[PDB]
Amino acid sequence: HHWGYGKHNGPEHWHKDFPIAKGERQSPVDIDTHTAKYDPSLKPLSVSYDQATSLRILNNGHAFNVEFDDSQDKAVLKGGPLDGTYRLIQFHFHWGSLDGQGSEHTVDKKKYAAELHLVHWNTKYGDFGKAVQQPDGLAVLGIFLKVGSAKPGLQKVVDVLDSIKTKGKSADFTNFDPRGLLPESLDYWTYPGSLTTPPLLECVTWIVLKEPISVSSEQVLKFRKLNFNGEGEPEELMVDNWRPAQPLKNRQIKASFK
Ligand SMILES: [Zn+2]
């Protein structure tokens, strides 16, 4: 009986195996747009993904990750509230069983159909494993997805899901350009938080974009066809793999815009 999102191993049970679940800087949180502070000292984000090298896509049992080669500064995030260079290692999504839920972060209590997380780690720490043990170890770019028009840049991802239907399956996934997943504007909210899945370490600097991207009902429907289970085990659709909002606990959310 390990963690999951079902009735018996869901987010509400995680604190038993991971006490930090009830910690002081847990994520996600609800972003109250009228309480967030405009901080003009925040620089614009600098996303250099031109030399990104995707390597494979994997179904790990709780979501699907697209992994990148992070052995060099090929795809990096700088600027904003960050000190130093953060390398992109993987990206994944959080989605629901219905279009009205799925995102982890909420804006004025509004839930989106899904949320994309682009995970980066601070290079001063040498590797992802060391970075997660530091308060400024990770930088995660969060992007909301709403249902409407199709996103062409996401179709390549949608088309291969069939080959990694169950837990443990992986497939080569080269030459995917993550720049096709970015919205027009890079305005954002930022606050110090944690990973939203166990081990739930409080090593993340969250950068949540104001502008969501649109995907079609057909694209999100294919996400819902994935399984939490491994091949040959009873089928459990991979849906609602999101953690609900946690207490802000006197943290302050800053906005790069007004
Ligand atoms: Zn995530």
Image (cartoon, helix red, strand yellow):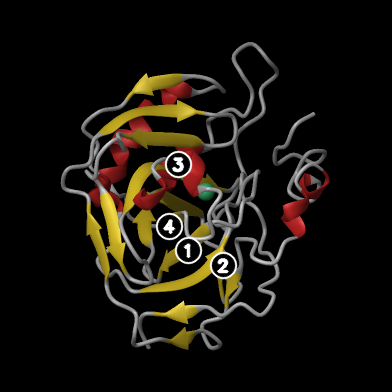
User: Circle 1 sits on which residue?
Assistant: 206
User: Circle 4 sits on which residue?
Assistant: 139
Q: Nearer the viewer, mark 2 or mark 1?
A: 1
Helix, strand or loop for disc 4: strand
The first of marks 4 and 1 along the sequence is 4
Which quadrant, please, contains the C terminus? bottom left
**Could you tell me the amino acid type at mark 4?**
Ala
Which quadrant, please, contains the N terminus? top right
The image quarter in which residue 176 lies: top left
Q: Which mark is residue 128?
A: 3
Disc 2 to disc 1, C-alpha distance:
13 Å
Q: Nearer the viewer, residue 232 or 78?
A: 78
Helix, strand or loop for disc 1: strand
Mark 3 residue crowding within 10 angstroms, few (<14) / some (14–19) / many (20+): some
The percent coordinates of residue 144 (x first, y second) are 44, 60
Disc 2 to disc 3, C-alpha distance:
27 Å
